[PDB]
Image 1 (tube, rainbow over the protein chains, first blue to last red):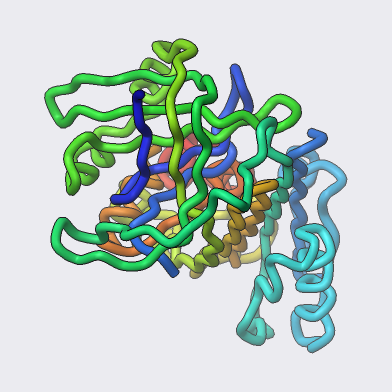
Image 2: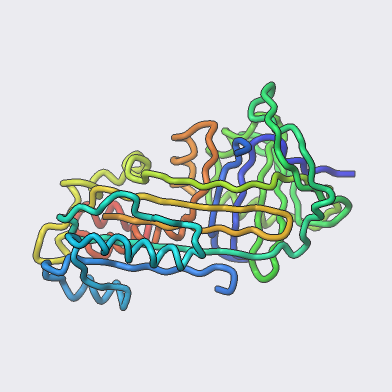
Length: 31
Length: 245
Length: 46
């Protein structure tokens, strides 16, 4: 079973599919 | 856009004489104002507050200089349900490695056995995986997760629009279990220092030449970006606003 | 992605969340009133 476990710093992008980037972030730490 | 909406507003001091070429390029997003009047900032802030469904408020947190000549603002707003929502039943406390030997509690959302667009990417600056979590409609969240527990910085600093498109294009449907934090974050950024470091050395302050705005000297001394995001089991909500003045 | 990378590298270990289009829209307004080296430096962001 493959795993995607975002339990260490990651980047996340909100985008239009086939299109532009709307927002981009780095998750470094729990707030 | 249906999930994403944007607006821009430009405010010029009423005592300045503006050039029509500039005004034509701006469109019907321009008005003149009196920056010596205190309710002026209140009315601009209320505009952004309402547009961003309360999430950016106030954009302008300092009284405005009565000598301001031009204020340019943008605001954007996004809210969409996940195409496949997370089950709260599966959300629980997990260690988050802020560094390889420092663990901080996070509320982790989990989804098992479903299929998502995904790729395993091998690069000289680090190996990683990328997944796409779709929203209802035509947007998605793409997440980039280093294979090494503290491997993000070298990938981050090689993230370009072209790379990102290349990795995203390589994704294919695969069954994979997904674990990602639930989180809310607010940001506030002074963009002047970053943009100077990127080469905008004659944009802010006295070297800035905005002589094509009007018959008078216009200077832009500051530029702020304020943001909000809420990622939870049912939806993502995001907002941002930018001001230069 | 250049603005994101710069902000991120400027606040190591901190969360970062930005909207590139929002930022580009204000830089584009500046570009319309700009002249000389100022316009040239802003044109990449329009």
